[PDB]
Image (spheres, rainbow, N blue to C red):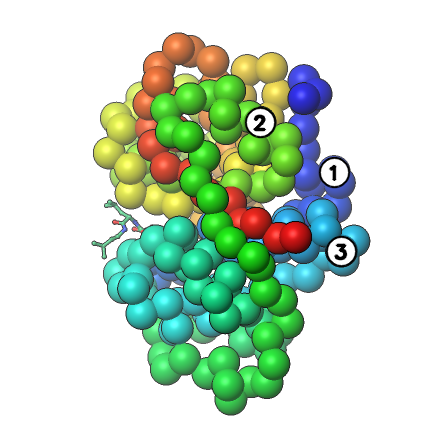
Amino acid sequence: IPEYVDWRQKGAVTPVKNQGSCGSCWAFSAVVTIEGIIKIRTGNLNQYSEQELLDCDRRSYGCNGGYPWSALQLVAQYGIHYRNTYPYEGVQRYCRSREKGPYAAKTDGVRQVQPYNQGALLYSIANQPVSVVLQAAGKDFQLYRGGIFVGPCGNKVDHAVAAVGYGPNYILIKNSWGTGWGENGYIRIKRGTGNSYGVCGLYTSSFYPVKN
Ligand SMILES: *[C@@H](C(=O)O)[C@H](O)C(=O)N[C@@H](CC(C)C)C(=O)NCCC(C)C
């Protein structure tokens, strides 16, 4: 795998979104991955519906939090609509999939990256954008204004994001707090410090969609 990876440069990442005041981080994260894999597999870059996940993944708790793995299982079993068909409203409403026509895309499965192992995550990332979680509750994470983030931070994961690249000493993450946060809405998190949890516990739980 290359020393530097940036799916943004391969045209496999769509613009940065804002989840607003709805705990929909999990939906956001899952979509970053679907968007990526489709581009990688088909050559088209489409935006997919986070709202669709928010309203339809009954295993998650809407604006109260959720599971990227669950969201991703949903897309593999049923499929998902384009973002314009089912735009984001930042509030949970009934599932309108059928109301909206046939799904735009379907994946084949979901896989877990072996946890607390940097090498395994970098490998996956080299393959496609991956759903990852970290501890975002601390003020330092929140007031992040750019640079290589190194903490301070515990490993009390509570936020789902997506890993879209890496370099020599960091992992490139796409957040969903708007373009006004961090590095134009991205964060470069320090990698290779030997902490098995990963900084902010970045290696606790990572998934990615499978598409034949
Ligand atoms: C992320 C966001 O801010 O949207 C969101 O809070 C999330 O999905 N988070 C995990 C939060 C931690 C505090 C553990 C999560 O908790 N997942 C399930 C949450 C609830 C019990 C409903």
Cβ atoms under marks 1 and 3 closer than 8 Å: no
Choose top left, top right, bottom left or bottom right for residue 38.
bottom right
Mark sitting earlier along the chain (3/2) = 3
Q: Residue furthest right?
A: 43
Question: Who's the residue at 55% across and 15% down the image?
Answer: 169
Cβ atoms under marks 3 and 2 closer than 8 Å: no
Query: In the drawing, does residue 10 fall left or right of residue 163?
Result: right
Q: Marks 2 and 1: which is nearer the front?
A: 2
Question: Who's the residue at 39% across and 73% down the image?
Answer: 56
| Image coordinates for residue 50, horizontal then vertical, percent | 48, 64
Q: Which residue is mark 2?
A: 123
Q: Secondary structure at mark 1?
A: loop
Q: CA distance from mark 2 to mark 1?
A: 18 Å
Mark sitting earlier along the chain (2/1) = 1
Q: Which residue is mark 3?
A: 42
Q: Amino acid at mark 3?
A: Thr
